[PDB]
View 1 (tube, helix red, strand yellow):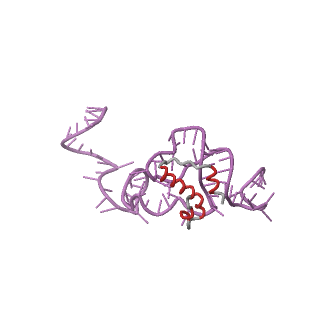
View 2 (view 1 turned 120 degrees about the vertical axis):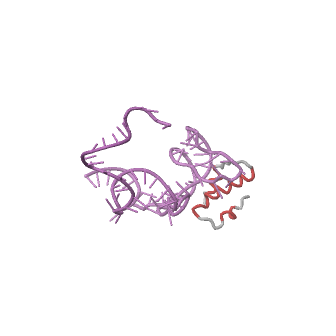
View 3 (view 1 turned 60 degrees about the vertical axis):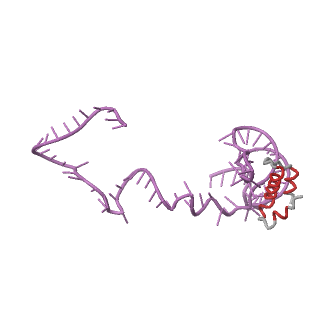
Amino acid sequence: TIHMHAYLHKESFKKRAPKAIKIIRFLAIKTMKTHVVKFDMGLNQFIWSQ
RNA sequence: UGAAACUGUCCUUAGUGCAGAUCUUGGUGGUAGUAGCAAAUACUAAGAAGAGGAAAAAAACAUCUUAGAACUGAAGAGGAGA
């Protein structure tokens, strides 16, 4: 569970959803140790749903 | 180094000696990898093509298709003329 409110608190509005993608990519790099991260289309569409 | 013309003495002649003219023309520095590359709301994921996203996050990746999210808002960032 990624508590994304922690990362995006008091963030610039027009960079909220794009930064949500960046933070998830960072968490995959620091956990699976792989630099090649591929997002499912369902995950990207959920981030931008709002 | 350079590869085909040149020098010394005597007279003669002159477009004959440069550090300056905010001198003319051409070239080049320090400033300096500095000031900047900030109006027009905004981009994201998957795939293709390509030498052109690599990597101890080098956090950014131009074009095209699809999906999401958007703007001009119909006296328009539309379709047409002088």
